[PDB]
Length: 285
Length: 286
Ligand SMILES: CCCCCCCCCCCCOS(=O)(=O)O
Ligand SMILES: [Cu+2]
Image (cartoon, rainbow over all chains, first blue to last red; front, top):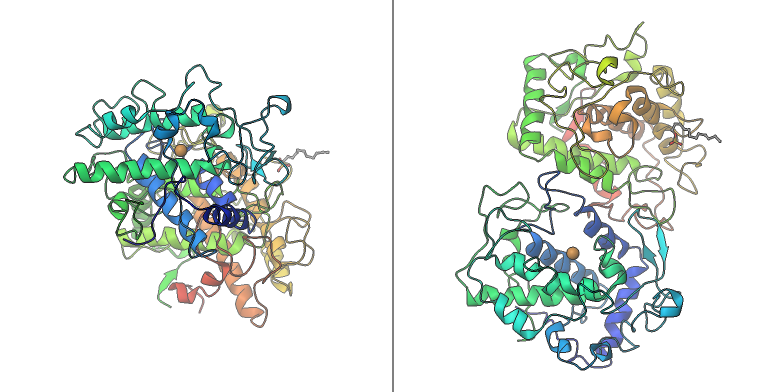
C-alpha cells in the first residue's frame, strides 16, 4: 500500500506548489473536463431510471464510485507528476476553528479563498480564480469563473464536526434496503448525509456553495476532490473497524448498485474497489 | 477475422429470432441502458468545451467512437449468446424499393414497423412496441415506448442513395481541418452527412424519425446499431480502398480527436480500433 495520501495541513509548501500545478496541467490538456463530465453523466443515470438513485449518489454505489473516480483521477496526476498524490480535506477539524474560512486550505497558493460578494461570489484569489481557471455549466457549455460562498446556506451554516463523524463510524450496516435516500441505520446514507439532511458530505457542498452545492457541476471546483478524499478515507476507516462489514447489497440491488455490477460510466465494480490498499494507496496513517 | 457481421437480409430467421431475443436480455439486464447513456453523454461532451465538436458526432472521432461503441455492444451480445453478431442494415439498397418501408427489416418478427399516427407515432408492432419495450429520454427517465415516423421530414424524405455511398468512398482524405461540420473533402464529414446535410448517416437518422431523429435519444431504437453497423462497414470498405491513407488528425488535434487520445467516455483511442479485424470481426464480404 504505497502512494500515501496526506492531510492537506501536513503538506509542505512545495507539495502544495506541485499539486495545484499538476491540476492546472490536467485542466488544460483537456483531461480535467472529463471528470466534470463523468460526474455529471453518472447522475442523470438513474438505477433504475426514474428512481431517485443514480449510479453514484443516493444509493449504495456512492462510495466506491467516488473511490475509483478519485483513483483514476490520481494516476493522471501521477502520470504528470509521479510524486504528487491526492490529499484529503479533514473538514471535521476545520469545523472547530473560530472561522474555518481561515484554513490553510483556503490560503491563496492552493485553491484560493471564499467568493467575493461584489462579483456575485466569484472567487478572485488563488490559482483557480476566474481568469486563471475555466468552468463548465450543466449543459456542457462554458460557464465563466468559479464561485464559492462558505456557510451562506440556512440549511448548512457550518461544516460537519468530529462528533458527526465518530457517530457515523459507529454504524454497523454498510447500507440497508431499499438502498436510497431513506435507508436507515446505513453507514453509506449517513456518511453521504441524508439522515437529517444535510449532514456530512452533503453538508459541505452545501457549506461551500457555488458549483459545490449544485452537485452535477460540483467537480468544477478542485476541492471537490480534496473533499471526497476525506470521504474516502473515512470509509477506509469504517472499513477496518467493521473489517467484517462488507458491501451490501450483494444482489437484488438495482442493476448498478450490487457488488458485482459495473458502475456507469466504467465497467468497474465495487468488488474492484473494496480495498484502498490493492488500489495501491494508503492514507497518511 | 472470425466474427462475421451479416446483412440483415441474409439473416436466416432463427438468426433474427436469436438476435432479437438477446437485445431484450441485454435490455432486461439493464445492460442495454448503459448504451443509451454513453451515447447521450459523449454528445454533451464538447471538445474543446463550448464548440460544436462533441466526443462522437461533429468531429473526426465519430467513426472510431461509434466503432468502439458497437464492438463493446457486439461483445455484450456475444458473452451471452456466443453465436450472435451485430448485423448491418444496408439502407442504400432499401433506398431503391418503391417504398423502402416494406423492407423486411421492419418485419413484425424483427424490429417492428413504422409509427402509428393515431398514438402519436408510437411503435405498436414488433418485439419493440410500447408494451415490451421501455424508452428513456434526454434527462434519463422513462418516457413511454418507441416512436418512428419514416421520412416525414421534408429535410429527409428519402434514405441515402446507394449511388451516394460510392461518391463518399471516392474521397481521398479521412478528414480535414478544422475537423468539424464544415470540413471539406473529408470522408468522415461526408459519411456523417454534413456536406449539404442532411446526408447519409445524418439522413438515415432523420429518415426514421422518433427517437432516432434526435442525437441523444437515438440509441433507444435497436436499429441505431444496425444503422451504425452499416456505417462502420462503409468505413471499413473505405479503409481497404484507400489503404495508404490513415486517420486524421494525428496530433495538433482537439484533445479527444487526435489519433491517440482517449475518446470520452472511454480510455480507448482511434488507434485502438483502426483495424476491425484485430477487433475480431469482419463483414461478410472478405
Ligand atoms: C435560419 C433558418 C434556420 C434553419 C433551421 C432552424 C431549425 C430547423 C432545423 C430542422 C431540423 C433540425 O435541425 S437542427 O438545426 O435542429 O439540428
Ligand atoms: Cu458527488
